[PDB]
Image (tube, rainbow, N blue to C red; front, side):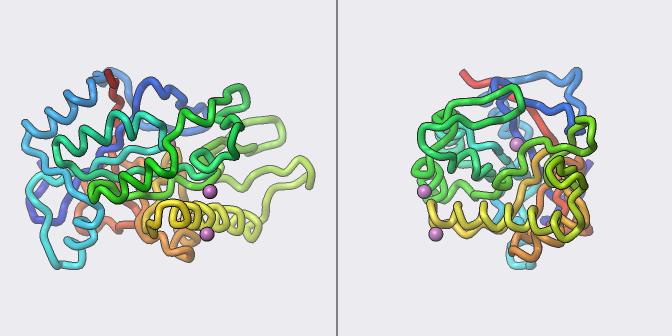
Length: 264
Ligand code: NI
Ligand code: NI
Ligand code: NI
């Protein structure tokens, strides 16, 4: 298995099965014949197998050669910013003293008061399904949680072609019905840049936190989005490619595994 070198780490992205919005357009990693366990049981598995959950700060420090990672290091991440992240996950993180990354879709968290969040063309959810800014700031101030961008409004599908086939918003040059054309490279870069910039500003404004990482929705990213993320200062990126993060893996291309859980 993985070399124990104070540098190589695994990342585990946790998804609550009751937030069942998975996407057609997205090309997610295979989940078939993988057992869904409870979150508490997951935290107990982590412990008993000898994993040592680490923070993003610890990753950065190991790369800079200041402090090596502990053995069997793992990064836990919780994206999308649903309310259960605060009421269920947060007190377990505290009880086990495990750090985590929480990645915020800021157009969801920051939606106008009294309005519903549209997730898909046929699905809207109440504003209060999501953690409040005050709740996120509290997690950030606990010392246990690193806040990250899950984009502002890239956590959805956009039109890839005239008929109606969808692709992830961040990856594709989107087709514009009003223009009668696709986005050009300049337009595309501008849209993704403004999105990332907005999510970082909103997070800093409301929590005081300067983020330094992006968790790409649906693992969708490319050369252009990585370059643009770098321009806005987000030099840490998390993908859906699985595998060990060995020293030759750039922190812009962090690998992670996806696992589903149930809460009680
Ligand atoms: Ni997500
Ligand atoms: Ni501001
Ligand atoms: Ni506000």
